[PDB]
Image 1 (cartoon, rainbow, N blue to C red):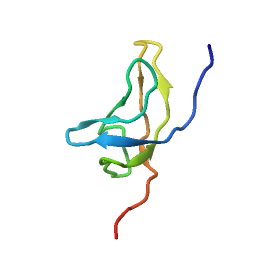
Image 2 (image 1 turned 120 degrees about the horizontal axis):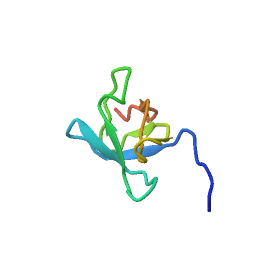
Image 3 (image 1 turned 135 degrees about the horizontal axis):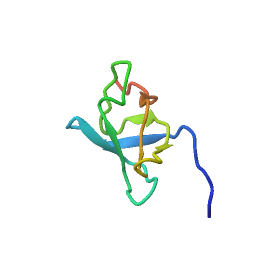
Image 4 (image 1 turned 45 degrees about the horizontal axis):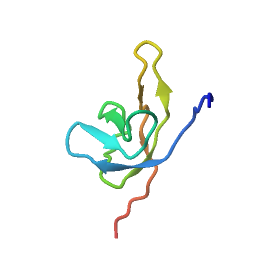
Length: 79
């Protein structure tokens, strides 16, 4: 019913080619999430299949949701 779901989450990215990418995480009407290169910090690159931990922040001014402080939690997967 009515419950505030706040906190860090974990999801993998679908495809990252342009400055903006979509994450495989459903928060509302949309199935995927929307984040910009400005979000990610510490000089990190998010690719397809990269699990990153982001915080769900709801905007009261607009009324939409997005990612913030995107941090690549997934491993290197190189070898």
